[PDB]
Image (cartoon, rainbow over all chains, first blue to last red; front, top):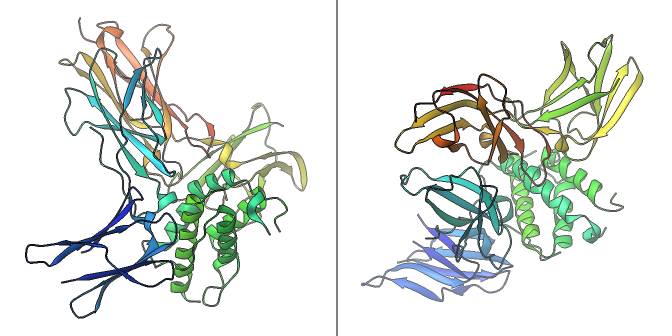
Length: 170
Length: 108
Length: 195
């Protein structure tokens, strides 16, 4: 199987001897600007620049020029954002905790905030969601220690179902 | 018509919470390469309206689909002065959905 | 002849539910009917089905876009009509399976329940309101606001060797869908240990 990821709307990474051609819009097809190669030299993937607009057409061809994979979507269709840069936690007088983070440089992301008792398991994460750039987690005990982590998750209605969430913050 | 006077905030909320689910529901995972794109919200709405509400050969019922009826109503309600092969239906539906994505990503 | 209405999304499937009733009981629904017109998908209007003191329709026909006129009618006479949008009268579904467990090691009570909206299509995110107080006697309820389906109560917050009553409800939390608090869940009870 082949995989495509658009990292933070900056680059597009295609991973699968195969050759890749690409174009934005209806211009001339162009070769992959930077293949990933094995020790013998068989291609393992490709990185190319991401454009915020225009349709990215992908054509992956086997040794023989036979089509093995084709695609045509906006680059953002495969969006994987960078994680939020640095998370802040502020106890409110309400007894709630306000979680905040810096905004991404583009719209259409939800943020998933997870928390758990610091003693708890990796299967004890509680999740809440909301838009940029902060949200509130209630009902927490002020004397216990909690772990928090965040990732950005592209909205399905905004970017489609082929987009994916960032890695979790530390 | 010029969709530039539309209340895009209201329309966005309608799409995200209703029309989007209708489109994906009809497509059931089926997908196609897109054909046309758009670079502004008004321009995207223009393509969306045309693709969504004008019937085409092989899918005469497209404008009668649930996602389509809601779209017509959303424009009427939120824009000033606004007036069979299943595979074909899906193809057009896929195009329309992708135009919505462009709409969401485009500037006002 | 004034009335209220609330809606509930994705009740027993993809279909949505509209419920209306008169404010004044001690009234007679003598041949009176409720009719909703406008903002429907396949039909022009719908007439609700009467069940005891309330009127309801379960349907997939709601556009959930724009306002509808809901009219109390007698034959062909409109007694009273009000314009309102289904998406602005949304009643959340009540949570279920409310449960409380004492955790001695943590010296607290862990409260869990199931959130039906999580399984729904349109309104997946709701805000919850957990309420508790001693089962016997008069007391002001303690409320806890959550968006998730677990929480903890510290032991010290409660009196020891007592029985508590607890229940939970939900309300929409969405930039498009608005409305009303759900019915309260069934109440659970639990007992507190010695300090």
